[PDB]
Amino acid sequence: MFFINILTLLVPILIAMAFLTLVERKILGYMQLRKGPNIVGPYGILQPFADAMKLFMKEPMRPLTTSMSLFIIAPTLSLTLALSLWVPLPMPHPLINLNLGILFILATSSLSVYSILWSGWASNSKYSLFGALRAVAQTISYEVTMAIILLSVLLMNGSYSLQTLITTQEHMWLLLPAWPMAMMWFISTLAETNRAPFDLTEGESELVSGFNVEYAAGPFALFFMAEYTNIILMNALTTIIFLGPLYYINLPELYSTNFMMEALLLSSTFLWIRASYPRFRYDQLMHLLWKNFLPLTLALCMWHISLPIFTAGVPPYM
Amino acid sequence: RSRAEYVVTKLDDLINWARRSSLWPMTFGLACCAVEMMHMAAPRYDMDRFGVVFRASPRQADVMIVAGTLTNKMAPALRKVYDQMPEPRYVVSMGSCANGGGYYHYSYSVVRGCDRIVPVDIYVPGCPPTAEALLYGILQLQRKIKREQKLKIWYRR
Amino acid sequence: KVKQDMPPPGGYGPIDYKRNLPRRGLSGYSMFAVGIGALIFGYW
Amino acid sequence: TYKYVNKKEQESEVDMKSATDNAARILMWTELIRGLGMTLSYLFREPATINYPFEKGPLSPRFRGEHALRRYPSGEERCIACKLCEAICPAQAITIEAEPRADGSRRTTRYDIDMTKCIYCGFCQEACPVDAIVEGPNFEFSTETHEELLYNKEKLLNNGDKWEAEIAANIQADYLYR
Amino acid sequence: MNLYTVIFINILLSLTLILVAFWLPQMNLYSEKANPYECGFDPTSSARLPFSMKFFLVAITFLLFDLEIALLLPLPWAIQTIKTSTMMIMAFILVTILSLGLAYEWTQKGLEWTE
Ligand SMILES: CCCCCCCCCCCCO[C@@H]1O[C@H](CO)[C@@H](O[C@H]2O[C@H](CO)[C@@H](O)[C@H](O)[C@H]2O)[C@H](O)[C@H]1O
Ligand SMILES: CCCCCCCCCCCCO[C@@H]1O[C@H](CO)[C@@H](O[C@H]2O[C@H](CO)[C@@H](O)[C@H](O)[C@H]2O)[C@H](O)[C@H]1O
Ligand code: SF4
Ligand code: SF4
Ligand code: SF4
C-alpha cells in the first residue's frame, strides 16, 4: 500500500511536469501573438509525449574529453533529487512526515546544484564550464538569504515541520503578515530554479547552452524533467508556506483542490515572467541579493524575532 | 506478412511519428535566407505549433537548415556542427546559395551547393524562399520521415 | 483619364507617432499605507 | 532639427511626495508590473497565426515564383529564341540553343534554367519581348534532390501548360503597369 | 524505512531511464562527432586550464555567512525559553554584528568583483 502511494505521487507529478512543458509553450506563444502546439494531439496535448519519445530514441553523446562517471551521474542525481523534494510535502498529508521537513528541503535543494556543477565540469568543454561557474555564483547569490527568509516566517510557525504550516494559517494566509518576505522568497525561487530572468547556467544567447551543452538525447531529457519538476515543487512550497489552502479535518480533498489551484497559478506566473523580462547579468544577480535582499532580510529577521516577544505571540512548540 | 511484421510496421509508425512531431532545428543561419527563417518562427506561421523548436546546441538538434550562402571559409565549421548532431539527423538546404551557389555560383570564395559538404534531405528553392515555402519544405521533410522503414528493414535482414 | 495610385483628395487622416505611455497607478502613500495595513492586521 | 532622447537632466529638489513615489516604484517593482500587464494583454488577444496549409499568406499578381514557358492561344510556343532573357540573367541561370524548326520556325532546342543558380529576380520576364518566359505564382516546389531543380525545356513547357490559367489571369491584372 | 524506500525508487527510476537512453538508440561513433563543441571551430586549449574567479572574496564571505545562519536556525527552539530577554539580546546582537560585517565589506568594495 505504501508502494501504491509512491506511484500515486510520482506518476501524477511526472505527468504534471510533462504538461507544464506544453502549458509553457502555449502561454508563451499566446503572449507572443502565436498559438503554440496545436497539431500533435488535440490542442497539442500529445506534444510532450512526442518530445519525450524523440529524445530517448536519439543517440546519446559520448564525448571524448569527458570524464564519464560524473557525466552520467549528474543527470541521474538531478531527477532523483527533484522527485525526492516531493515526498515530505503535505497536501495536506505527506507521504513522508518529517519533523524538520523545511530543513530537508534546503539540504536536498542545495545538493541539487552539484548536478549542474559536475555535469558542466565533467563535460570538459568551455561553454559547459562557463555554465558550471555561473551556478557557483548563483547559489552564492540567493542561498545567503533564502534560509533567513524562511527562518523569519517559521518564527510564526514555531517549527520546521511543513504540516504545522497548515495549522499556522488556519485563519489567515501567511502572506498577510509576511508579504515582504513572500516577495523576496518568490524572487529567490526563480533564481533557485534557474528560471528567467535568472536563467544563467543555461543562458542560451550567451553560452549556447551552458552546463548541458554537450548533452544529447535521454540524458538531456533528465535535466529538463528535473527543472520542470522543481518549478512545480518550489511554487507548491510557496503555496503551502504563504497561501495556506483551506483545511478542514473532515474535507482533506478540499485542501488538495485549493492547493492545486494556487500552485497552478504560481507556476503560470513563472511562465508569464519568462515572457516579459530580459535576463540579468550574473554579477547583477549577486548584487541584487547581497545589497538589497540581504539588508532587508536581516532587518526583517530581527523584526520577526522582536514581534512575538512584544506581542506575546510566540507559537507553540508542538 | 505475419503478425510479427504487422507489429514491426506499427512500431515504425510510432517512432516515425515521434521524430516527425518534435523536429528541433539548430540555431544556425548564414545570410538573407535566415531572415525568412525568422519569419517562419514569427506569429503568422508559428513553426512552434508544428513542434519545431530551435535549439542552439548541435547535441540537442535534429535538423540543420542551411539558410544562406556557404563560403569556403565557413565550410569546415558547417561540417563540424553537422557531425556533432546526434543521429537521426536531417539537412534542409534553403535557397539558391545553399542549393547550388545561386548568385555567387561562379565566385572563387563560395561552395557551389552545400550538398558538396553535407547530405541534403530537402532542397527549398527561391532567393529567398518565402517563409511559407520554407514551411512547405519542413512539412515535406516530415512526410519523408513518415516514410522511413528502419524497423521493417531490420526485421527482414 | 490618367488613373494612378494617389492620396485621397484632402489627404489622409493624421498619424500618431509620438511616444504615448499612460500615467497610471496609485500614489506612493496609498501603496505604502495599504502594505503597512496588511502587515499590522496580520501581526494582530 | 534635432531632439534629445535622454536629456531630462533638469535636476530639481525632491519633496516627500516624489521621494515616496520613487521609493514605492523601487520597492514595489511598479514598472516591472507594467511589463506583466502588457504581456497579459497579449494573452487575451487573438493570435495572428494562420492555419497553414489550409490557409495561405496573401500574395499579389506580381509575385515571382516558379518559371514557366507560355504559348499563344493556338498552342504555338511564344519563345522565338532571341536570347534576351539569357543575356540579361544576372545569375547566368539560363542556357539556350536554337535552330530552324522543321517548318522553318525560329525555335529553341535547349531552354534550361538552373533553379539553384536563379535568384528569382524576374529580369528574364521583363526582358522577354513576347511574354514567353514568366515567373509563375507557384512557390511550393521543394524537391528531395538537387537534380530535380535543373529544369529543361520539357519541364518548363509543362509548367506553362500546368499553370497557364492562373498565369494568364495574373498577367491580365498587371500588364497595364508594365 | 519508508523514506529509504521512496528515495531508492527515485534512484531506481532515474537509473533505468539512463540505461534505456544508452541502450535503445542506434549509435554511430566517430571522432568528429565526439570532439568537444565550440561553435564549429576547434578549441585552442583544454577546458581544464585555470578559469579566473572574479567573485572569490564574496565566495569565502559566503562561507562565514553560512555559519551565521547555522547559528540562527535554532531560533524557533530558543524562543520557547523562559529567559526571553537574554535570548532576544543574543539574537539582536548576533544579527547586528553580521550586518556590521556586511556593511564593512560593502564599504571596502569587497562585494565588487575584481577586474
Ligand atoms: C571474453 C571476450 C569476449 C569477446 C569480446 C569481443 C568484443 C568485441 C566487441 C565488438 C564491438 C561491439 O561494440 C559495438 O560495435 C559496433 C559495431 O561493431 C560499434 O557501434 C557503432 O559504431 C560503428 C562506427 O562505424 C558503426 O559501424 C555501428 O553500426 C554503430 O553501432 C561500436 O564499436 C560498439 O557499439
Ligand atoms: C552593538 C550591537 C547592538 C545591537 C544589540 C542591541 C541589543 C539591545 C536590545 C534592547 C532591547 C531589549 O528589550 C527588552 O526586551 C525585554 C524582553 O525581551 C523586555 O523585558 C520585559 O519582558 C520580559 C519578558 O520577556 C519580562 O520578563 C521583563 O521583566 C520585562 O522587562 C525589556 O523591557 C526590554 O527592554
Ligand atoms: S539564396 Fe538569395 S536570399 Fe538566400 S542567402 Fe542566397 S542571396 Fe540571400
Ligand atoms: S529570375 Fe532572374 S536569375 Fe532567375 S532565370 Fe530569370 S533573370 Fe535569371
Ligand atoms: S523566353 Fe523570351 S527572351 Fe528568352 S529566348 Fe525566348 S523569346 Fe527570347
Image (cartoon, coloured by chain):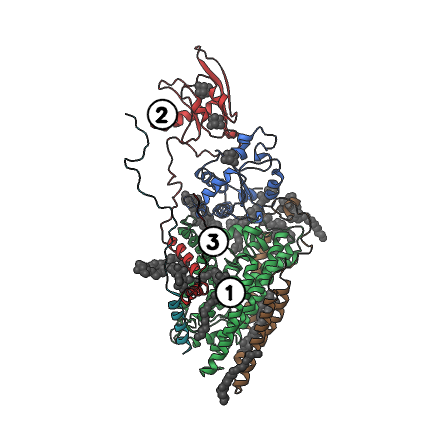
Chain colours: A green, B blue, C cyan, D red, E brown
- Classed neighbour count for the residue bearing mark 2: other residues with Cα under 10 Å, few (<14), some (14–19), many (≥20): few
Q: Quadrant of residue D125?
A: top left
Q: Are marks 3 and 1 on the same chain?
A: yes
Q: Is residue A35 left or right of residue A95?
A: left
Q: Is residue E72 visible?
A: no
x and y percent of residue D84 in the render? Answer: 47, 19
**Which chain is mark 2 on?**
D
Give coordinates of residue E19: x percent, y percent: 59, 56
As displayed, is residue D66 above or below residue B87? above
Amino acid type assigned to the residue bearing label 3 in the image: Pro
Q: Quadrant of residue B88?
A: top right
- Which amino acid, mark 1? Ser
Q: Are marks 2 and 3 in contact (CB under 8 Å)?
A: no
**At numbered mark 2, what does the secondary structure look like: helix, strand or loop?**
helix
**Residue D20 visible:** yes
At mark 3, the secondary structure is: helix
Query: Label 3 to label 1, Cα distance in Å?
Result: 28 Å
Q: Is residue C16 above or below residue D26?
A: above
Gap in Å between the C-alphas at discs 2 and 1?
Answer: 66 Å
Q: Could you tell whether D37 is left or right of B37 in the image?
A: left
Q: Which residue is mark 1?
A: A188
What residue does disc 3 label?
A48
Identify which residue is drawn at 46% across, 23% down: D154
Which residue corresponds to mark 2? D175
Q: Position of residue A116 (x, y in %)?
A: 59, 59
